[PDB]
Length: 238
Length: 208
Image (cartoon, rainbow over all chains, first blue to last red; front, top):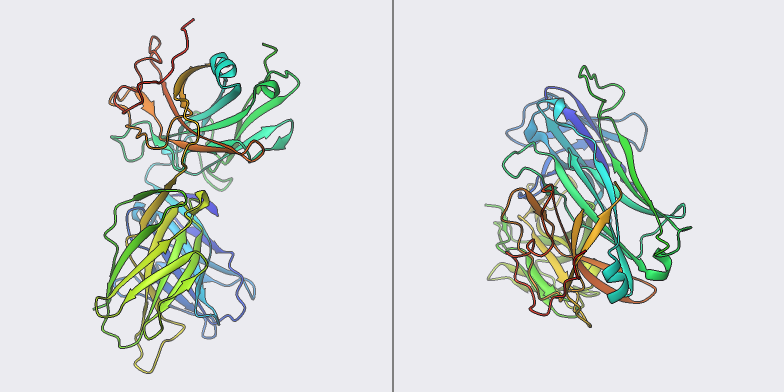
């Protein structure tokens, strides 16, 4: 699963990670939130050409084939309605249509709308430590756009997928605005004796997908590129 | 006319209990296929089961489809309903064009999709609201029964998330949790959850 953020009136590349046994026709689908997934086009591998659905402008979608098994869909003149999850698909001998991974696209008019997340780690309440005997630790990232974020817990230099939970989709700091920044929260729960050990290191790591080196940024502040932002804490003696 | 419609609003069903997803289609073709797919939160599209037009009712693993040919209705049913079964589910139709049979150029016709969020049944409810201190703060609502709804904040200045299921694979202990915070300096952890319906036995720490 990949994340791509692009400004309007530009080009975007969508990569297909699908492994195809027999390569004949490579289908492209688009899934937009609150709508049904639909095929935009498919690629004829033998004839090397694009077959577009009715109503689509020629030249809008182009699938490039750099290598034998490689397929990349290129979009032209990006508009905000191009935003969504793009899948590559193929039929198989089993009479099933396989969809390789997916990639979420977000197109914005102003590139000034992208913000890196501000992460903060919050120490467990002593009450729950006494009452429940288990300490709950909370990390939350705020003021980030677009929606693309990956939150990971790191304990003592190692990632822990157990005893951790994250919200399925981020909140909206400003529900009134469509381009408004997002807020996400996560939880990590460990035993009190493990939390009360000061040698134990706790770090909330958040992967953010921003601008690239090719993207131009003329603004005064720091360039909102693809960035890693972490907030760390140590165990309490009590 | 080739179409697929899923009317269902997001459905919530507890673990170990059965849930049924309704999908109805309209097709002019004599022979066809119906597909069900599972879309994970990571946006991974996964195949589930396929129902043939002239085939009998398809049942594979924990998935089962009730097929009514005259009614043009397929219903997917998940019996066990694990926690990992929470996903948006889609109903698809194989779309013919050529009259002589299906082609590899043909496409799927997708419904709007129906999201399924399973509720873990909580063995030992211990509803409480704890206040967490930052490193420089946040109120936390945990250990509450899954039968409890979480209503989002009325005030735009305060933010409230939804329930989140934590599972410790060691202790085999599962918990629901919610997070609420605000930029207000004097905001308190007693008032925050007022809009949501909460147990009367909910514990609060002695403030200090």
